[PDB]
Image 1 (cartoon, rainbow, N blue to C red):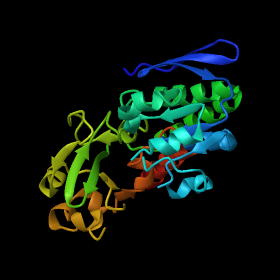
Image 2 (image 1 turned 90 degrees about the horizontal axis):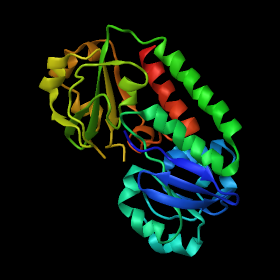
Image 3 (image 1 turned 135 degrees about the horizontal axis):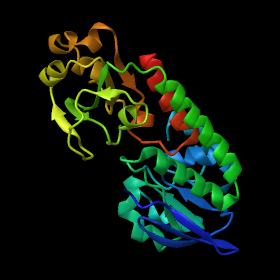
Length: 285
């Protein structure tokens, strides 16, 4: 299990430990550089927009209120821009853990990792830890309750005898993903059963083809199409007689998920996580 963020109050600051290291973070930080899009959404949802001084502007359609913040990268980190903003806090997730030592020379750097084996507990701890910095625990607990209620509404309507498959299409490559993966919340949080519970743990997933999809005969197929960031599109990759024969194709349950949520992994967002939960619920209702 990923080590959680723990914080102890030391008056003007918190002593913060997370899986990457320890930091003294000032209370109410006022110049925050955020490289994780999900946590940027949570800043919005907690009304902390004025605390943010840098984002990866090179930005999905749901985060356009930050389009005029100074750019610190693309998700490609620009260290010069970061230093020149003189931040009092840098927030990162998985995709930037490789940059940790360099960012930490600039300013205290908080890791809000999403644990693919314990998604909801990581999500809660990330949101509540950011809130504690600002004394917003009450407000963050109300919104965390809203998301839990949405998960319960979504779970309530899932069919126990149907099975789904998750795939990522990248140009013409198809790769399968299962429980406890980067897309795992379809199986792990919303309880939708998988066609294969034993695809191997790892970020690149398992290479598959249409024969595989036919062999599994999924009731639903969830597609994360990284071609939508061209020409070739999952719909054409799956435009064939193998995929056509599948229960998913026959009942028009090939679901194309918005990659600006799923591929960019905005699970740390109070509002973005909600939109993802609703997107699943509305596909299988």
